[PDB]
Image 1 (cartoon, rainbow over the protein chains, first blue to last red):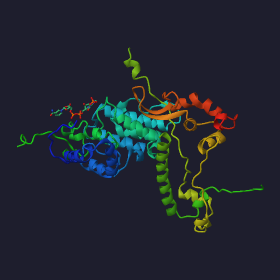
Image 2: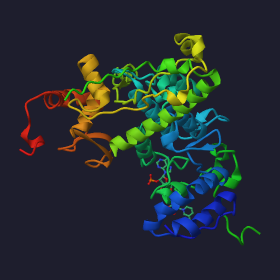
Image 3: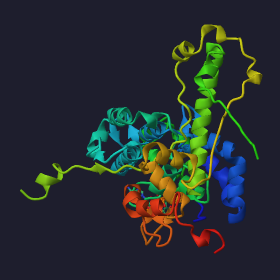
Length: 212
Length: 48
Length: 145
Ligand SMILES: NC(=O)c1ccc[n+]([C@@H]2O[C@H](COP(=O)([O-])OP(=O)(O)OC[C@H]3O[C@@H](n4cnc5c(N)ncnc54)[C@H](OP(=O)(O)O)[C@@H]3O)[C@@H](O)[C@H]2O)c1
């Protein structure tokens, strides 16, 4: 909303500052062109420095949703939303995101009306086994990039208001400021749910005089 | 107007006996990547 | 026993979505492909003088090469063929955004803008697709009256 906030100058916040000066201040007509032009730079900074990394990053290689396989998408969702240290989903709504995605996979790859291999999202409390089970039934989903329809559905699911904001940036478009800035305060209390448990990615509110 | 024609098409797998395993495997990988990019293009194009 | 007794007993059904494929040729492992041609063929041909077809398409009375082949080979459309034909014929259009409040990603009826599930394309459109495809009475609207 354009309101000043005093934050510790972490890499994350220094990236936020830079984007305030160079991206978020631009008028609407110049935003999408600037994102397209700086795309590779923006992706590298998100992945290096920010608490919401670029979603479509597979083994350190920047992609797009359009150039990820269904299996790569499922595994990236588990990597970013499922906490190995506590063996749980950081938020139940993130488990529901991932289960809703795995059902889309079955729908896209099944030849006939069948039973979901994920009857309850509780099965996702062992997420690797659920992924293995869906992609063994539909092994074409390991080799095919997202149908363009499934990219749109995935991005529609990222904007579900009855859900904790996804902890990643899934696209560079007009909503980039919202993806970047929304729900930015919980990470400093839950470093276990941040990419490298890295504090330097996070937004910590703190006053410059009180800091003495 | 007496336009007669004939074409003979041969199964593409007879081409691959003409090349080495390394050439074939390089080709298979390139085609696999191109096919994935084509599906991407096709579905985007169809729906938009 | 109430709803909780039968909620965990009830089970979720997956309806298929059309996943249209380009049908690139299948490439066999080298060992299999090596057995079809004679061994002497390796290095024998000038491959600059071997002509291959790398792509093909059509526009005809049965749509594209994919839909015409389904009709020619099988006499009926798969789910992929029906959705392709419904798209070709303008019966369905894609929609991504708000539709009567709720956010929708998928096919809608081109006329009414009502959502259409892929599984319903056949029941909703197949009769129309088959009546307005192939060899049929001349339609004056296609030929300037
Ligand atoms: N005065 C100050 O110094 C100060 C400092 C810190 C924060 N604040 C205030 O505290 C409020 C929240 O701060 P913020 O920085 O976190 O703003 P924000 O980024 O806009 O807020 C987080 C938003 O994410 C959504 N959300 C988070 N978890 C969710 C869940 N589990 N399920 C569904 N939705 C979820 C909610 O939005 P939806 O309801 O839209 O889904 C919520 O409004 C703001 O009004 C802010 O101004 C003030």
